[PDB]
Each structure stands twice: as structure tokens, then as C-alpha cells.
Amino acid sequence: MLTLIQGKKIVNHLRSRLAFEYNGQLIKILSKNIVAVGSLRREEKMLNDVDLLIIVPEKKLLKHVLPNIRIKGLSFSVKVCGERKCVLFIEWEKKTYQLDLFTALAEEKPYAIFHFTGPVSYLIRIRAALKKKNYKLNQYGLFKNQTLVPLKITTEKELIKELGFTYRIPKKRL
Image (cartoon, rainbow, N blue to C red):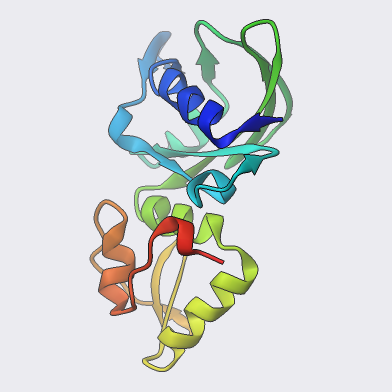
């Protein structure tokens, strides 16, 4: 049970302590590919769990990075690991901290993290304003009507700005 402040420090250390195993060598993940989700992204007071979104560049790497991801400096434990989502408990500073790692393609990296935090009430309202124009968004990109229509989205803000929706601060996502 760590606070938003403690986890903020946590992500800082994690930012330089997360890498994948490809070709026998440890490939570190650029700090530019790290986004916060859930309450941690909504500057919430306390957070029960810390959901981190990893950006997988290559296609195969998506199912390569998650399964071959080692941690240096911190103690981790894998309990429920899959392909796109992995559950592992890591202990740091002689204490245990819950850390859930989930990967998303470069296309859903901005969209998924944004639609990660939500919550449901915030997500449902989001679609309402977009529905007026016939646009949808979620770990995949911007959809038109009911089919994935390719939209240009870079970084993260582009996903919302592109839809022409009123951009709101992460803390204002309720």
C-alpha cells in the first residue's frame, strides 16, 4: 500500500531498471516509452496497485518483450504471465510492491494508456462526446462508427486532440 508520492519515485527507479532479453543481450527500455495509468495517472491520493504500460516497437517483440523481461536492482516474482499482460510481485527496500506489466503496440501505446485509467464512468462519457461525431478510441486507435479508421496519433495527447474532444488533465478523469 504505497502512496502516489512513493510510487512516483518508484516509477523513476523503474524507468532505469526495466529491460527485455532479446538475442541473449539485455535490451533496456527508453524512458520515452513509459506512461502511467489507473489512479497513478489521475494523481489519486492512494494507490493499491501500479499499472505500467510498456511500449513494444517491433511486432514480434510484443510477444517477445513481455515474456523475456528481467529486472535489475529490484526483486521480482512472476505469478500470472501471459503475452500482452503479465502479473508479477516485486519487493524493493526489503518490502513487497505489486507491479503489473502490460504491453501495447505503438498504435495503442497512447490510446491504451489514456483509456487505461478511465475509469468506466469517465470512459463512457468520453465516447458520448465522440459519438456525436462518430469517433471511438481504445487500445488500438481511433475508430469511426464501428470500424478501426487509421488516425494519426503521436505521444499521447494526439489521441484526444485528434478526436476533437475537450482535452482534460489526467487528474480530471472521473
